[PDB]
Length: 126
Length: 130
Ligand SMILES: OC[C@H]1O[C@@H](O)[C@H](O)[C@@H](O)[C@@H]1O
Image 1 (cartoon, rainbow over the protein chains, first blue to last red):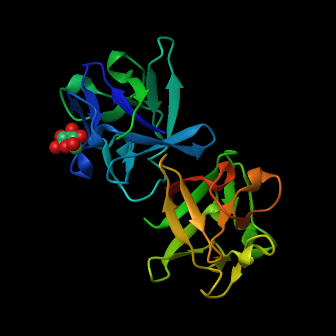
Image 2 (cartoon, each protein chain N blue to C red; image 1 turned 90 degrees about the vertical axis):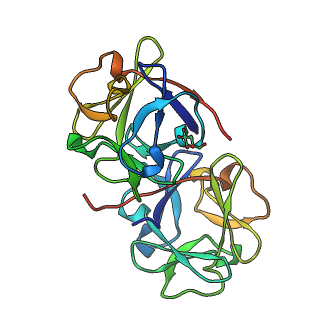
């Protein structure tokens, strides 16, 4: 299924069409804010963005992207289901996807879940 | 590696080439090397699927279970890539019949004439490169 991910700053995770880094900066979920959750096997998930490419952790080396033409790895995630119904995403490197409060592009370099690393999600299409 | 994909049945198992050895099954718990298929352009808007053994997936015209042991493309090895309403995909062989996971209960087939629950697959492009 296709979902949007809403970050700590109340904006939505934006694939940026695979140009440059991903950001948590959109006011409303539209095509670029819809991600197909992929069952990558063994509790791991991947995310296919609007451009048909896959979200990568970049191993924490740089801000996260949505440009990979195929899942390997840096593109599989643990989908952690939090107490409050939110989700966190843990990358290949054991670090957590962070919305960075919209202050900078999204990262996967933080070793623990805090506010910025919890997302509200709901299924949506079109 | 943008055209090498896996196919996941709604039974949550992945389509498996069986490395040519016998019929294909939708029973693998994890998308491994036998679970990856390169989508080859077969012309006229049709596609072929080449398994890990470098050979081609065949419908067998629905007369027996599907196999991945053809050296080259003809047909029973061409398929329509059907994109479904829900994000899943289906594959319609040259006989007009659709590829079925058979819910992992028997080997994969291509003899059912319409798209039902076992003829819809989740897909993703994946690579073994690490
Ligand atoms: O409507 C498709 C996309 O257009 C872009 O210009 C916006 O930044 C995205 O947020 C939107 O999802």
